Length: 292
Length: 290
Image (cartoon, rainbow over all chains, first blue to last red; front, top):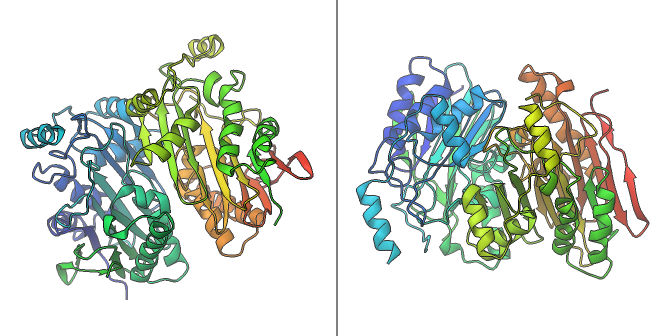
């Protein structure tokens, strides 16, 4: 029994993103195309205020985006702190496919996007501009309604894994701040002989623990996807305590999928959900949480 | 436990270790020792792949990458930063003074200047001449001391590490390698050990190299065994991607809680420096490409 094809993505907007990925997966399409099409739906929508277009700016009023992608054969691409391109996941795929590098940032990422035909656009909506000027008159508090990242991982009809992660980062972050979403091993990791995992939340904490590489290595060690996500969250809980911080101030979610299409998730604070679509249909599930 | 002890990469690790030992031999923190050690090399214009004499990207811009990690999971990083000679110290200020862990590009430079660092021209006349003559084949060259990574265990039994580079010569503007990425160029877990990487950064990111080395030591591997199996994982992936191993070089050095240390690389000719109470010496690790 292998449950394939199957796709998982983060937060409640993962349900709609999964319908676009299933359009690829249900026709035998590649997991890489499915996860790119899925997260682009959310990058494109200005009402999703933490991914792509309409994302809240850094404190200087610049919308800078972070994304990475990984396919079934350790090919990776990433862009971080890139301005004026609505679809960072697709520029990350072009870094992977068209350059000898795996990560470009800042002005160099934008110059490369324009060289590959991407269109320069104004990503700061009137809504985000209004909110930023009011904020100008930094408290990255936990908020369950803030779907701060879309991460999506899929196992296709060929039995191949791939994943994508994209965000506009912490609202009113310092100029040039980069979170976990464009870092391979922190926001996203895919090993086609084992499984894949993506992360959400306070990016600094996922980088600190190399979160998604740790989840996949625990599945390599025999942990179920859910057990792997749970123990990686418990490692963050331990480190939060050793650093003298308070867990109520921190939110991190992990979703994971292995080679047989088994899946799981776990988070620090209640209220993180994820969407799963497989042949039985698309549904929103609620994982366990550490802060009780 | 054999402590204090410090390891750093390549030939120039011997001189960098003498500066870190000035801190470690007096009971100083491993964090200050590894910062002082790699700054020696950032400061030297004759070291062409670290800080000040570093070879520019293809547009003639010297852009630097660095990260630091202490004994209690605190981390800081700057990538693709221009005009500041000492990126390891701006990384330490990201760690200590901001709510973030990584800043890049113009925002990293703006933060450095807000902290007192001075803007300097890092493109030496030598590097400028070489770049205009070059105006990309990132070959294996054992004379190219591409990164300095340094890891130390101090008198308190605490681990810390630093990694800094100017990255691949004539890289695309905006390219970031493994040296500022926690878990790829550098990782430190004070209950286990620490490891740093050198070489073709893209390959270390792909395998999340130094987090893998430390997790293998967590699983009971020796420092040398952990470095060897992480190199063997890169060998395997190079083969699955249909690539040729002769085109790639990666080195790992590692240190555990007990002060045991080890190293391994793909191609012969990588060396590292160890300084402990027996003195400072240059050792040569095993290599995969036989």
